[PDB]
Image: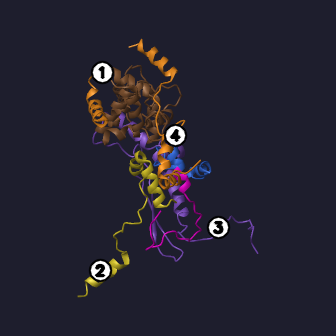
Chain colours: A purple, B blue, C brown, D orange, E yellow
Amino acid sequence: FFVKIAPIRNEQDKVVLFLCTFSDITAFKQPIEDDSCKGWGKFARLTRALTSSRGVLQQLAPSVQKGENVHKHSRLAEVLQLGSDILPQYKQEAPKTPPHIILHYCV
Amino acid sequence: RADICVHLNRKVFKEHPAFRLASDGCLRALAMEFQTVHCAPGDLIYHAGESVDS
Amino acid sequence: EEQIAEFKEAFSLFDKDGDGTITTKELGTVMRSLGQNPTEAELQDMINEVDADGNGTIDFPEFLTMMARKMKDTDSEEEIREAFRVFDKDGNGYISAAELRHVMTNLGEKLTDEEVDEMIREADIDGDGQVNYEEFVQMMTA
Amino acid sequence: VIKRDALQKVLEFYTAFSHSFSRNLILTYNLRKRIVFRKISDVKREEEERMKRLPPDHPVRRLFQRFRQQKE
Amino acid sequence: VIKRDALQKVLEFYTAFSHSFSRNLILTYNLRKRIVFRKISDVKREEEERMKR
């Protein structure tokens, strides 16, 4: 598991909650098994397990070689983005509106 | 009325695994008794000490 | 049985050309993408190991047996599943009254139609003239 | 229509009438009782099947026995 | 939400269903049960105290 840990701050600036995102590195890292019918079977199982990363995010990767250089890292980049998106701080905040827009009920 | 109630609690009965096996009559019975509450942000439902009756 | 049908996506992904036959070249490519470079001989050996026909390839049906072998369900589950299979002559996840009657006849243990109906009613909860897997499991446990 | 509880109360109040009521009132159809029947299509199918065609009896044998026991 | 009494009545009425319901419905969190835990600050304080006496 690619465990991407992150501590969450608060509206009072203190740390209160944790976050920890996961991702399967079974087929990507290396093969080990305690009991199995064959190696091929094991591989298949691994593939089945690791569908979210290899299926939708790294879908241009299965043609081109050396996925550990770019693909896995790229996948981890989602987590990195999350690191920013997992700084809302669990604070009872106002509704988030983008800039260059004025509210419906403003003064 | 029963039908209406069922329709209202479609989010309950279709999602949860409890009521998939439930009969139609049973479902109807349930629906009649099911309330629905629209709680606000920062509005607590159960308070420590209060009676857990639902 | 059910989740094995959702596996087909993986198979599709594996196939580069899209012919329903996993070539060695494709496998090699996949391996390369992953970041591991084994020899073609190894791949060939692997192919030989699982596939039944042996035409330098294999289909989803071929894989199926392997998948089944891999699975390894529970003992109770295995028993119950077998029983279910025996009951349901067609094999559509549901056991009709007629089907039940037929199976009884096959067995030898004769009973009345009314009795059978009663049994069915006892089994069922939702009331659709049929019994689910969960419903079936109710009778075997208690 | 009349709610059963109220009706029951009434019957209790008028004891001599209750018996008479019981004697008289034949329900056109009870919703309590099951009806035993087969559909014709199903029968036909069964018949059709008839012309076509022990080890797993032990898991089901127990069940059968249980059913029999229940029956009494 | 559903009031317990009504639910109980319903369950009683539909006996075969009740068992199924029991089997299925896993509460995400029981409000009856206590949780056993200590706060980290308190633990730290305790540790600090440890060295004194």
Q: Nearer the viewer, residue B45 or D45?
A: D45
Task: Please tell me whether mark 4 sits on a helix, a strand or a loop.
Answer: helix
Residue shown at the point (45%, 25%) measured from the top left: C59
Q: Which residue is mark 4?
A: D24
Q: Residues within 10 Å of mark 2 (few under 14, many from 20)?
A: few
Which mark lies nearer to you, 1 or 2?
1
Task: Please tell me whether mark 3 sits on a helix, a strand or a loop.
Answer: loop
Residue shown at the point (53%, 70%) measured from the top left: B44
Residue shown at the point (49%, 44%) measured from the top left: D20
Task: Give, as a three-letter code, the residue at label 2.
Answer: Glu
Q: Are marks 1 and 3 on the same chain?
A: no
Q: Which residue is mark 3?
A: A95
Task: Give, as a three-letter code, the residue at label 4.
Answer: Asn
Q: Residues within 10 Å of mark 3 (few under 14, many from 20)?
A: few
Task: Give, as a three-letter code, the residue at label 3.
Answer: Pro
**Mark 4 in CB contact with mark 2 (< 8 angstroms):** no
Q: Which residue is mark 1?
A: C108
Q: Position of residue D35 (x, y in %)?
A: 47, 31
Task: Give, as a three-letter code, the residue at label 1.
Answer: Gly
How far is the residue under mark 4 from the one under mark 1?
A: 47 Å
How far is the residue under mark 1 from the one under mark 3?
A: 71 Å
Q: Is residue B32 above or below residue C80?
A: below
Q: Nearer the viewer, residue C37 or C134?
A: C134
Using the rendered image of the protein, determine whether residue C104 is visible from the camera's viewpoint: yes
How far is the residue under mark 4 from the one under mark 3?
A: 72 Å
> What chain does badge 4 belong to?
D
How far is the residue under mark 1 from the one under mark 2?
A: 75 Å
